[PDB]
Length: 232
Image 1 (cartoon, one colour):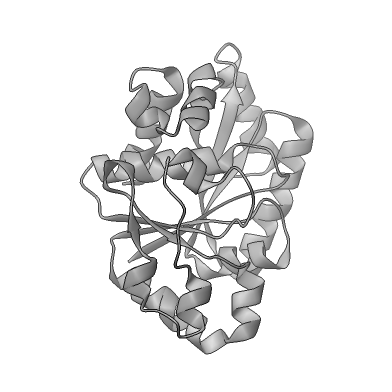
Image 2 (cartoon, helix red, strand yellow):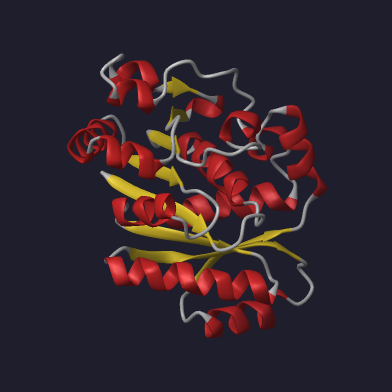
């Protein structure tokens, strides 16, 4: 019923980390959550969720080789995952109608649908943004990252996707306050999450257990469930 796309400007902000743990934190709060991994890249949801290879993807479901139920897997903490298999652009050109109904079937199966959009502003990304009602923008406290994020914000507004708020990932807790105001001023939007730089989210990735479960008290984890609370 609630569809949110997580997107960013450049390619290395750490958004997939936020999407995965956000979903796990959301599921831990009792919400029926589903993440559709639209980022056909290495170091994605499968790695961070510590999940084993996923056989059936949407590409299979769109080709009529399988039922959507077969492309929905259960991950850590109860979060569900749906692999796109092929870029959204591809699925969309293959059959626009089918793609929409399948997305509908998915929305039916949950309360919250998170779309891990591909890195930047490619066709597949804008499609992901337009497909959601809300956009969760992820940026780093670096200028380049913040301006690239502004373009993403703009695209969402051009399309009619409402900005849920912006998440600043990997900030040093020292200046935060001034930084937050500064960032909110640059891309005129509200930051609803400040995830401090944390070695633990890197080790979480390397070993396959989301920080939210691996290290519940690390500052990154607490910041993320904090964000899931705001969102839910």
